[PDB]
Every structure is written in structure tokens, then in C-alpha cells.
Length: 262
Ligand SMILES: Cc1c(NC(=O)c2ccc(C(C)(C)C)cc2)cccc1-c1nc(Nc2ccc(C(=O)N3CCOCC3)cc2)c2[nH]cnc2n1
Image (cartoon, rainbow, N blue to C red):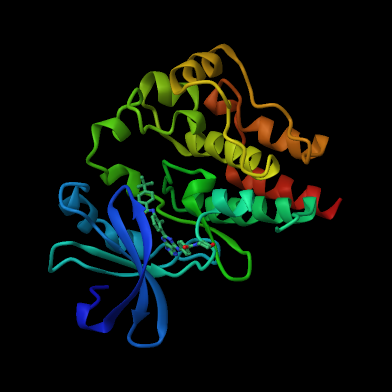
């Protein structure tokens, strides 16, 4: 869907990300939207355009909904559902006095979105709490799934670059740049750890380079105080050295529902 830019009103600046400025606005006068304004040189634009229809067909309650794009102009606009509470990481760190039931509910929200993406054989490639958003009701939804592919920035795309998500990557991504549904599984386990530690930085006080080395040897994130033994077993299963020994999102989602019922 090609949104006519005359149907958008720009109301507030939401901040800056990898692709530049993001604004809050209204679409067709009534619908609350976030609008990414793609800065010149930051994206592989023609590749993104010739695949944006697939991304629009991605529709799930726990996925930030893509409403449309403005591609007959520069900057390109990406118009999505608005999430009033911003990113999950900053949200975890904030007054909320979270209960363990709420922490699992957040894991479930993310897992449902990821099981849906897995069912469509679509990789997120940068799953982390900083890339999940929270709405006015405290519902967590995953955002910017598949956009990692289109980043034009060597510090981000190189596994040894300063911006590469090393702390959310499995050994086969760090050593061989081998992305799969199993590399998103690993990132999900790290995200579960971010949630249960209330937004702590994974492998705190260690650099990306030391993290890459330690993970390859077998170091794993400690069990957070707020994680039960059952919850830790689930996030730990995501970090198997062998990608084929890691569960699928179907299994994780089923395991999370089982813990919830217990
Ligand atoms: C996502 C994003 C980025 N990042 C990128 O664009 C990006 C990320 C990753 C990559 C890859 C490819 C590298 C992976 C590429 C690009 C930067 C800025 C905003 C947003 C953003 N913010 C939203 N809502 C907010 C935000 C803030 C506040 C606020 O001010 N608050 C919070 C509450 O307390 C008070 C203060 C309230 C609501 C959205 N709602 C729907 N979409 C939204 N997008």
C-alpha cells in the first residue's frame, strides 16, 4: 500500500534510529501512526521497496503492523501502528513494580509474534528488547523485523562491526554469518533474559569482542533472580551450541504456555 503523503500529519518527534528520524502523526485524520523517515544513504531502498508487500502481509496482534509506505519521494516513509510506551528495554528499566506473571506475559507476546514469523519463514535478524515496542496497554509487540537486511552501514552489517548485535548472536552467526530461524531463537533467549533481569545489559562489563569469545567457549547468561527454574530452562534451551539442538518458536511458545498454566 502506497500512502499518499497528503494523508499524513506530523505531530511530534519520537526520536532517531538506524534510518534517521521517526515521528508520531495521524493517517487519514483519525489513525495514530509512527512514521520512519528514511535518511539518505542509510538503506538499500530498491531492495526494501521490491519486498515491502510481503512485510505488509505480515499481520499478527503481537507484530507492529505496517500500514503502508511512501516510495514516490525522498525520504521514503514507513507508516506503522503507533506504540505509545516506546521500546521494551527503556520500559523494563522504569515505577511498574513488575510481577513475575507480567514478565512471562511479555515473553509470551514476543514468542507469539516470533512463532508467526517462523510460520512464514521470515527472519527478524535483530530481535532484542530495544527492538520490541510497548503500547498504552502494556502489550509488547515486535518491531523492525526483516529491516536489518537493508541497512547500509558497515559498522552494523559486519559481525565484527561496532554496531553489530553481538550480545544477541549465536556462535554460527558470529563465526560464519549463518542466519536462520535458530539464530532468532538464540536472540529470543537473550530477550527473555533482558525481561527477567529488568533490562540489564547482557554480559555486563565485558566488551562485544570478549562476549563473542566467551559465548563460543560456552559461557552463558546467569539465571536472573526473577526467573523460576522452569523459566530459566526455557531461555537456556535457546543457547545450545548446536543450532539444530535449539527448539523452534512453536515449542518455546508451547513451553511458555505450559509454565503460565503451572
Ligand atoms: C523504532 C523507533 C526507533 N528505531 C528505529 O527506527 C530503528 C530501530 C531498529 C532498526 C534496525 C533495522 C537496525 C533493526 C532500524 C530502525 C527510533 C525512534 C522511535 C522509534 C519508534 N517509537 C515509537 N513510539 C514511541 C517512541 C518514544 C516515545 C517516548 O517519547 N517515551 C516513551 C514512554 O515514556 C516517555 C517517553 C513514545 C512512543 C513507535 N511506535 C511505533 N513505531 C515506533 N517507532
